[PDB]
Structures are given as structure tokens and as C-alpha cells.
Image (tube, coloured by chain):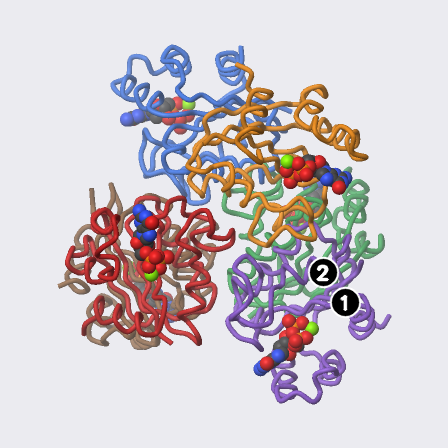
Chain colours: A green, B purple, C red, D orange, E brown, F blue
Amino acid sequence: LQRTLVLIKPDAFERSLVAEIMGRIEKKNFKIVSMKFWSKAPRNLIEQHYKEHSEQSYFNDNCDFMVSGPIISIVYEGTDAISKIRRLQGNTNPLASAPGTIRGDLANDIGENLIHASDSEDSAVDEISIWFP
Amino acid sequence: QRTLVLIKPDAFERSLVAEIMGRIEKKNFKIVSMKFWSKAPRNLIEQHYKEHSEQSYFNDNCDFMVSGPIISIVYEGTDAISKIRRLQGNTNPLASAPGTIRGDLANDIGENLIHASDSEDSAVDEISIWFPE
Amino acid sequence: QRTLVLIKPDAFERSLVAEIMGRIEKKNFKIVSMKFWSKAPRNLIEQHYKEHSEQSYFNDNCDFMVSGPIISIVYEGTDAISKIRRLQGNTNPLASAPGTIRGDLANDIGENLIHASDSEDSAVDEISIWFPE
Amino acid sequence: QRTLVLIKPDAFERSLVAEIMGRIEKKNFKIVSMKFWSKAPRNLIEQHYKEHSEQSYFNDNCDFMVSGPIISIVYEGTDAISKIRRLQGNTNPLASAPGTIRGDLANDIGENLIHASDSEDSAVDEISIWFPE
Amino acid sequence: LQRTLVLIKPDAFERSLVAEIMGRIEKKNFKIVSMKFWSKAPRNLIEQHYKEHSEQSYFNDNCDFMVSGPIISIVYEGTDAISKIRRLQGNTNPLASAPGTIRGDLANDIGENLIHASDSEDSAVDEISIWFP
Amino acid sequence: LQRTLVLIKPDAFERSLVAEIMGRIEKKNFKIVSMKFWSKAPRNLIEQHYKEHSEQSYFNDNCDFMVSGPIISIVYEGTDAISKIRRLQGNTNPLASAPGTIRGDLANDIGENLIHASDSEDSAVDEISIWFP
Ligand SMILES: Nc1nc2c(ncn2[C@H]2C[C@H](O)[C@@H](COP(=O)(O)OP(=O)(O)O)O2)c(=O)[nH]1
Ligand SMILES: Nc1nc2c(ncn2[C@H]2C[C@H](O)[C@@H](COP(=O)(O)OP(=O)(O)O)O2)c(=O)[nH]1
Ligand SMILES: Nc1nc2c(ncn2[C@H]2C[C@H](O)[C@@H](COP(=O)(O)OP(=O)(O)O)O2)c(=O)[nH]1
Ligand SMILES: Nc1nc2c(ncn2[C@H]2C[C@H](O)[C@@H](COP(=O)(O)OP(=O)(O)O)O2)c(=O)[nH]1
Ligand SMILES: Nc1nc2c(ncn2[C@H]2C[C@H](O)[C@@H](COP(=O)(O)OP(=O)(O)O)O2)c(=O)[nH]1
Ligand SMILES: Nc1nc2c(ncn2[C@H]2C[C@H](O)[C@@H](COP(=O)(O)OP(=O)(O)O)O2)c(=O)[nH]1
Ligand SMILES: [Mg+2]
Ligand SMILES: [Mg+2]
Ligand SMILES: [Mg+2]
Ligand SMILES: [Mg+2]
Ligand SMILES: [Mg+2]
Ligand SMILES: [Mg+2]
């Protein structure tokens, strides 16, 4: 049994895909245990969330995108939730994400890619602490 | 207008949260605030339904409303109150119309998936209950 | 209550069996009995529709009903008879409402996808026809 | 009967083209002609809506109708005109019924996703406008 | 042209996913040629169905699960139906089943995994003989 | 940014899957820039479209199928549209096409396979020139 942190990104709001994305996770039988709506996430939380990427060329653009509209932060719980939701999410690169995955079916950009999900136990604990202190 | 919607515990039990939210999303209403409650305080539920305090079902309904999670949402849109009420459908499963949320999904007078404010005055009161900030 | 539903041969031809069953399932009705007929005996069809024996369409309708498979289902739920009738929608394609099974999917008075018992008395008779056990 | 349907520019903006066409397709109407317009000529739009020429919204509506692509479709079926009108739903978002295209998807009196001919006489006129061949 | 044996498992009934599962197979153009509904399958048929696993640690628990609610047994027919429906079904292990498959999208447990499908021509004949003697 | 040529094949019309197929591409955020409806495509355009296969045993049967009902020719535009839509389409062979893809979910034959999509930049230019001279 694990908890993982998911962000529904501003592009999901713009494209009216919030329920579609949440629905794919819900139909897999994962349970919401925490959830917050952000009309606009604080820049500092975004920069902390993506701190690994702070020295990458796309960092500033990614952070700008992430504060360009609302986000939902959700903690999902289930057996092996972290890897399972990562599999559902699909590859970052739209040339690689498989049909059937959230990104494979719905995303068409490496940056505007609809959903974040924790990639490991350690990062899940870290990310949950950021969004749900 | 702004209206107050509750996703009720039966929606969680039946894994219909995204389905309900999706019907409102597809109608182009915007989420302005949202909170997740693992279990709403009974006092909050009693206040929300204070006008039913003398009804025979009052306690049973309060028990149901604290039996599982709730999501409270403020939606915004032109004439959002009446429009979301029409999408919601009648309380009575003998009357709620196919095509409405309750008409398609609810099969009980009490366990009826969704609350929506019924007037501007009740919207103000309910938003103040669920989002006192 | 228990009611008798037929999935008609046009549902098989048009690959709408799951769609129709899904609309009833999502309303939370429980299957109590079910039988698949590769081709129903004409005599069974004539008995089912015996009250239409003098109508001009009687033979054509019987021909249609044996033209492909049927699934007969007994569904159970509070006020299941009237509720499933409302989901079914009117026989006449000029009247069946969008949101109903026939309103959304049927475009003919005869080839109309689904039968549902219209009263408690007819439910008893029809269940005895299709499930004499 | 044959009727003239327009998929309006808001359907393109909101990525609802397939959703709308799918609702008509599932009702078993057959496409007899179809044209895609990257931008319809304003004169065509003015002719289509000539009966509204004195209305206060006439110019705003024409502006909207040339603001993005349109698909014009001739559909054929028994009583196709009235049936597709019923699927379409009322112009007014305070009236369009859940289960209809506008009832489920449209939230504005002007930006209302779909046109459908309202009579046999108007169907002839509109088909001659969009498909003069 | 082949026939294969599918079981819709009790978890599909509990989670109201029966039509969803049948619909995925129906949309692939497979035809139902036999079908039976079991309110509760006999223990002996279940133990025979899973006889290969009789000495495995999970055998008793699996059999208990399989008689814990209704099942539907279906014979589907199509060209290479056996391998095709196996592909649609997805891996037993929820750490392996691919998004897009029935289990990949809907199942979250190695035991409660929604659907059985024959794994070969020989086992299909055997399983059909069990459920449809 | 690329343009690719898609054909919706006559089997999609027969099976009422036109909107389903177009919807999968639309939800991926690809934009229609040209579209034509053919009640019956001219034999010569079909033979030119498939000229690579002119000496294969299935050529005549494939061409016969392709003129057996309507087709829609669509030009879609998006970043890397050619490879992305090919991925969505899925393998020609129904023993290989992955669940989650259009063919993996919906097609059950190597010939009647619902959709064509250009396989390269060069063939896209060629095919667009054929259908949209
Ligand atoms: N423009 C651009 N943006 C990128 C690139 N790589 C990553 N990003 C953005 C989008 C990602 O969602 C986010 C975090 O990257 P990640 O942890 O490698 O990917 P992911 O766990 O979201 O699939 O940063 C990239 O290569 N280019
Ligand atoms: N068991 C039972 N519960 C009832 C009955 N009438 C109302 N309720 C419950 C369910 C309703 O969602 C809630 C509030 O009643 P309402 O304001 O008349 O209905 P609504 O605005 O949720 O459609 O109280 C009732 O008659 N019986
Ligand atoms: N062709 C034709 N068929 C008809 C007509 N009226 C009824 N039928 C057929 C289709 C109906 O499903 C069946 C039983 O008629 P019903 O009990 O009045 O309708 P329903 O309970 O299936 O809605 O007989 C009719 O007027 N014309
Ligand atoms: N802004 C605005 N637009 C309107 C109003 N009434 C009609 N329109 C626009 C939207 C309609 O689709 C179009 C044609 O009006 P109509 O023939 O009465 O409606 P309809 O046949 O599209 O349902 O003109 C109106 O009252 N206000
Ligand atoms: N708890 C548990 N149950 C298992 C395990 N392996 C198989 N089972 C159960 C669930 C399977 O649906 C059933 C038959 O196993 P199978 O033939 O290897 O899998 P499958 O053809 O259903 O994908 O037995 C297992 O490793 N653990
Ligand atoms: N009957 C039959 N038809 C075939 C076979 N290979 C190809 N075809 C038909 C169906 C294909 O859609 C069409 C073009 O073949 P293709 O370019 O290799 O496949 P595709 O780009 O449509 O996946 O010709 C084949 O091996 N057998
Ligand atoms: Mg990451
Ligand atoms: Mg109320
Ligand atoms: Mg009747
Ligand atoms: Mg009009
Ligand atoms: Mg097996
Ligand atoms: Mg090719």
C-alpha cells in the first residue's frame, strides 16, 4: 500500500480534461486521500516541486506554464500506486507515450503534458510534503 | 453566478466522482474553489441541511453524509445555479430525467450522488459554510 | 420489483448490447436472471406479444424478433419497472427523449433495441414466458 | 428527409466535433454530403441567417460564425429534420434539456455548437446555400 | 474462425463493470454465440475450471472469490478469437498489464482481475465443455 | 509541424465508428485543415493511393473494399503528426495491433481496418496531392 502525488496541470483545465484524467485513475480503483485546488499555484512550490530540473533550459518555461492556470494536487492511495499510476501516465515525450496511457491518448507536447505523478517512494514523500505540509 | 456543489459519499463508493464532475465540466462551468473532506464534520452537515432538521430522514441523511468522503466545489458561470440544478435532476428517482446526473446514475431518494444550491440565497449560505475563508 | 428486459436483434446487429446493458447497470439495477437466445422460438415471441396479435405489424414484428439473437434479463430494484421504462424511452422515434436508450439510439418504431415490462402484471407474465423455471 | 447541419466554430475550439457528430451517428442517420470550411465566407453566413438580419445579434453572430472552421453536413433519415432538432436541443441554455447536444455541452445562447434545419422548406434553402452543386 | 470462453468475474459485478468489459470485446467485433448467467457458480465447476492451479497457494482463495458473487460465462466467436481476446484482457499481474487492456485500465489486483479468457485452442474446448456441457 | 493524410474507410461507416475514430485523433489535439466526404471514391484515386501494392494478391480485393462504401479524406496538422497518428492507428495485422490503438481496440481484419494514415513525409505530400489536388 502506497501513496503517490498527482498534479493535474493547467493544460487539463484549458482543454476541459480534468475529469477525463481523474476518471482514468478512478476506474483503476485508486482512492483519493487528500486533494487541494489551486487557482494559481505559488511559484515557489512549483520551483521546489521541479527542483531537480532547476538548471535545465526548459525550467523557467515549465514553471511559467505551471502557474499559467489552475492545478489540482491529489494524493492517491493503492497497492503499488506509484508505479501503477506512472504506467497509466505515460512517457513525457509524445513521440514515445503509448496509446492507452493518459499522455499517449491526450497529450501532444513534451511540456504541456496534462499530469504529474511521483516517480518513486522517496519523491512521493517529498512531493506530498510540499503540497500537503 | 457561483453555486455550491457537493459530491456525496455514494459517488466515492460507486467510483462516480469523475463521471459527475465530467458532466459539469463538459457544460463549460469553471471551478473557482474546491475542497476534499475525508469525512465532513457532522455539525457542518447539520448546518448545510438545517432546513430539514424536523424531517424524519434528517438524522439518517446526516449519517449518510459523514459515511464517506465529500468534495465541495464552487462553480461559476452565467446562471450557474439553475443550470447545474437542471443537470443534477430531481431528488426523486421516480422523476429525475434520463440525461441528468441523478436520472442516469442515482437510484435512491437519499443516496443521490450530488448536492447543488437551489437559489442565490442558499448558494451564499452554503458557500459560507463550506468555504468560510 | 422485478422486470423483464429484452435486448432485441437490432442491438446485436448494431453492436449496442453493452451500451444498452451499461445504461441499466449504471443506474444500479441488479441482474437476477439472464438468458441468451441465438434465435428465440417464434411461439415464444408470439406469446410475448400476444396482445398485439390483431395489429397490422404483428407478423413483421415477430419476423424481426427472430431475425437475430435476443438476451432476456430479469432486473431487480425498487420500482424497477417504471424506472427502466423511463430509461427505455417512448416507442415512437418522434417522441423518445434524448437521454433515453431509444431517444439516443433507436430510429425506428419497430427496430427499437429494447423491451421492458410495462406493469407488475405484465412483468409476471413475461418473466414466466422467458424464465418458466 | 434530408436536413442541413452545421458544426459551428465553438465545436472546433472546444474539440467537440466528434462528440457532436457521434451523437447523430449513434442515432443511425446517414451522411449524404459533407464539406469542411476553414472559414466560411461572410456572405454565406449572412444568407444562412438572413431571417435574423434585423436582430441585434445579427452581426455578432456572423462574426462568430466566421471566427473558425465549420463543417456543413447533409443528413438523411426518416423524419430527420424534427429528430435532429430534438437531439440538438433548445437555443436557450436555460431551456435545453440534459441529454441533448446543447443541453449537455452548450452554455451560451450564441455559441451553441450546432445548427440544424428547422423545417422542410428551410432544409431545402440551407442545403442549396451550402451545397449549391 | 475460433471460439473462446470468457468469464466475467464477481468483481466486475461488484464494481458495475460488466457492460464496460463486454463492450470492449463487442467493439472489437466479436460475436456472442453462447452465454449463461450464474448467480453463484457451483464450487465444483470453478475448481475444474482452475484445476491447473489446484496445488498453488492461492487456489482456495481464488475459488472462494469466484463464488463470492455472480459470474457470466460467454462463448465468443471470431477469427483468431483466442489470442485476440487474450491480448485485450491483459497480463494477470497489475504491475505488468498494459494501459489500453481491460486489466491494464480497470484491474488493480492479481486475483480480483475482472475477466477470464481461454489461453489456447485446447483449453477453450475444455472450458466450453465445462460451462456449456 | 506536419500535415498527414487520413482516410476513414468504408467499414467505419458500416459499423458507425466514424466519430469514434475522428474523436481519438481530436482528443490528441490534432487539427483538421482539409476534409472531403466521398459517397464512393473513384476507383482510379484508390488505385493511385495504393499504387505500391498494385502487384500484391490482395490489391483488387482491397480496392473493391475501398469503393464499397463512403470514405472521408482528412488532412490533419500537428507537430510530428505523421508518426503520432501512425502510432494511434496501430499495426495493420490484428494479431499485432496493440490495445489502446484505433485498430487494436476496433479492427478485427487485416483488410477491413478502419483507417489509413500516411506513413512518411514523402507519402503524406503524395497522398494529399491525390485527395486534395
Ligand atoms: N520543453 C521541455 N520540457 C521538459 C523536457 N523534459 C521535461 N520537461 C518538463 C515537462 C515534465 O513534465 C517536467 C518534469 O520532467 P520529468 O520529471 O523528466 O518528466 P515527467 O515525470 O513529468 O514524465 O519538465 C524537455 O526536454 N523539454
Ligand atoms: N430518505 C429521504 N431523504 C430525503 C427525502 N427528501 C430529501 N431527502 C434528503 C436527500 C436530499 O438530497 C436532501 C435534501 O433534500 P432536498 O433540498 O428536498 O433535495 P435536493 O435539493 O438534494 O434535490 O435530503 C426523503 O423523502 N426521504
Ligand atoms: N411497425 C410498427 N411496430 C410497432 C408499432 N407499434 C408497436 N410496434 C412494435 C414495436 C414495439 O416494441 C412492440 C410492442 O409495442 P408496444 O407494447 O406499444 O411498445 P413498447 O412497450 O416496446 O414501447 O410492437 C407500430 O405502430 N408500427
Ligand atoms: N446573442 C444572441 N444570439 C442569438 C439569439 N437568438 C438567436 N441567436 C443566434 C444563435 C442561433 O443559433 C442563431 C439562430 O437563431 P434561431 O433560428 O432562433 O436558433 P436555433 O434554430 O440555432 O436554435 O442566432 C439571442 O437572443 N442572442
Ligand atoms: N493471489 C494470487 N492469485 C493468482 C496468482 N496467479 C494466478 N492467480 C489467480 C488469478 C488468475 O486469474 C487465476 C488463473 O491464473 P492464470 O491462468 O496464471 O492467469 P489468467 O489466464 O487469469 O491471466 O488464478 C498469484 O500469483 N497470486
Ligand atoms: N488481405 C490483405 N490485405 C492487406 C495485406 N496487407 C495490406 N493489406 C491492405 C490493407 C492495408 O490497409 C492496405 C495497405 O497496406 P499497408 O500500407 O502495408 O498497411 P497500412 O499503412 O494500412 O497499416 O492494403 C494483407 O497481407 N492481406
Ligand atoms: Mg518526474
Ligand atoms: Mg436542496
Ligand atoms: Mg409494451
Ligand atoms: Mg433556426
Ligand atoms: Mg489462464
Ligand atoms: Mg501504408
In terms of image quarters, where does ligand 4 lie? top right
Q: Is residue E36 above or below residue B39?
A: above
Q: Helix or strand or loop: what does disc 2 sit on?
A: helix
Nearer the observer, D77 or E124? D77
Do the residues bearing badges 1 and 2 touch, measured as CB atoms within 8 Å? no
One can see residue A112 in this view = yes
Residue under mark 1: which chain is it in?
B
Residue under mark 2: which chain is it in?
B
Disc number placed over residue E29 in the picture, else none: none
Outermost residue toward the right in this view:
B133
From the viewer's perspective, tell me whether residue A123 is left or right of residue F85: right
**Image x and y of residue A119, in percent:** 62, 55
Residues packed near mark 1 inside 10 Å, few (<14), some (14 to 19) or many (20 plus)? few
**Image x and y of residue B57, in percent:** 61, 86
On the same chain, marks 1 and 2? The answer is yes
Q: Amino acid at mark 1?
A: Ser
Nearer the observer, D45 or F11? D45
Disc number placed over residue B82 in the picture, else none: 2
**Location of residue B53 (image quadrant):** bottom right
**Location of residue D35 (image quadrant):** top right
One can see residue C11 in this view = no
Q: Is residue E120 above or below residue D12?
A: below
Identify the residue at horizontal 36%, vertical 70% (top origin): C119
**Tag count:** 2
Disc number placed over residue B119 in the picture, else none: 1
